[PDB]
Length: 227
Ligand SMILES: Nc1nc2c(ncn2[C@@H]2O[C@H](COP(=O)(O)OP(=O)(O)O)[C@@H](O)[C@H]2O)c(=O)[nH]1
Image (cartoon, rainbow, N blue to C red):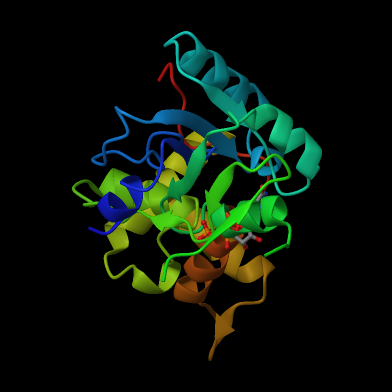
């Protein structure tokens, strides 16, 4: 209902998280306690390498099965990292925009009611990923889903979420300047002005957060295990 329907069909789950925020992009709530579970930390190419290294050992130390990967990693390498049992049947699960379609497409690759596809050794993978929508109870979670592009900028009505998101960004990257200074500067630098040469702060926020989520603002992670 409806990930609960799909879980019934599988014995293996691949949890596709964003490496920049492994906790905000975890599939909390939904139950994989009786499935073989691989934690996939994705988008390592746009994450802070050192932070990602900390996340790996954090999961390994917990006894958990964890891998890291990104768009540009070869299909062969991903498959080896995955190392699926020959009798695995697989659900790819996660929050929106975390790289699940891209992963399915690479595995697929492409070759040929709920649909499946098969790997060369016959392991079966569900063609469509289970999409997980979270109760956003904290503005911190909303901010973190914004930063990784799970929560699109068009959906943000509350300016406090933008502020929390910046505050997380700023701490991660080392910025000590204020919300106002930073966004005025960003609007200026990118020529985002309205009549009278007034910095368009709203366009600024929209472009900046779009760019952060795409990894265009640098290799930055938003959660640390330390923490
Ligand atoms: N930099 C980077 N971008 C990625 C990676 N995987 C996916 N993306 C991008 O993330 C966005 C969402 O990817 P998509 O596969 O459609 O996400 P989905 O909603 O989970 O299926 C797209 O803009 C992709 O181009 C990755 O490993 N690295």
